[PDB]
Image 1 (cartoon, rainbow over the protein chains, first blue to last red):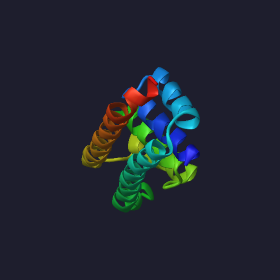
Image 2 (cartoon, rainbow over the protein chains, first blue to last red):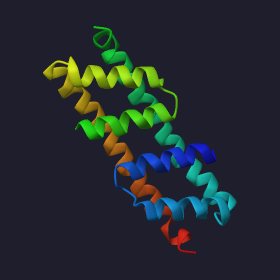
Image 3 (cartoon, rainbow over the protein chains, first blue to last red):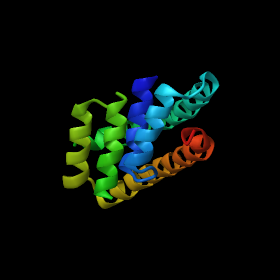
Length: 70
Length: 70
């Protein structure tokens, strides 16, 4: 979870939807003072995103592999 | 574009949908020998992903900001 949340927050930050400031605050909050249910809800959001990432990856691989190999 | 493609490929790699090997090959291919149309199609896939990232970011911010602030 924590590893997935950090990786996900990094993706967001790298494209400027959150500033480094919010990233830090989000992670400190998540780790220290997020209630058990708000963690469960964070996990849900991250899981949807993981599914979208899985899909893109499959798409890129499926669509371009043949070309990449030459 | 290129900056967005690299950032996007990094997100994928960080969660093991592609190995560092494919990342490198994908980027070299994209830059050097991807045809103009296959670039247009890559861009489309990346754009869908950018929309999914935008949404997650908004979701996290919208849902948790109040909590993060205390």
